[PDB]
Image (cartoon, rainbow, N blue to C red; front, side, top):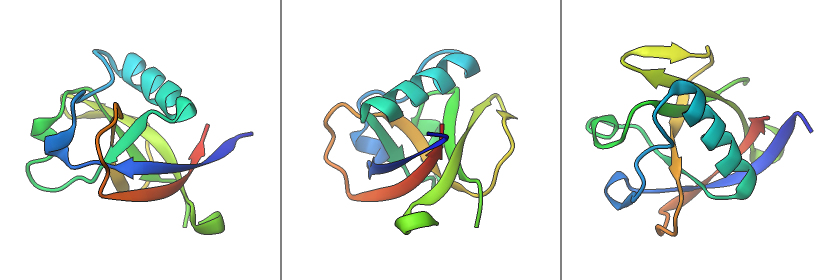
Length: 113
């Protein structure tokens, strides 16, 4: 399927144990997509002071369209030293590995895969 319904655990930035997916734009997009498939991906909502507490390159989920079955359609955009790789809509948050942190909420998304 071109899209997959996922329910992403929303994590507090200070709880996150593994603060990024790797060391290059290509690696972080690769690893984010693998963790999304494996159900091992969390979401951190972006506010003042969040991104400097995480590791670059960043992987964002961004709204790709204006919401089947409650699931917002999203795609992945990576960022490294102020350059983004991809073009999409509003940020829903930054993706991180999930390794058992307790979430505060779930974000229903339809991921363009």
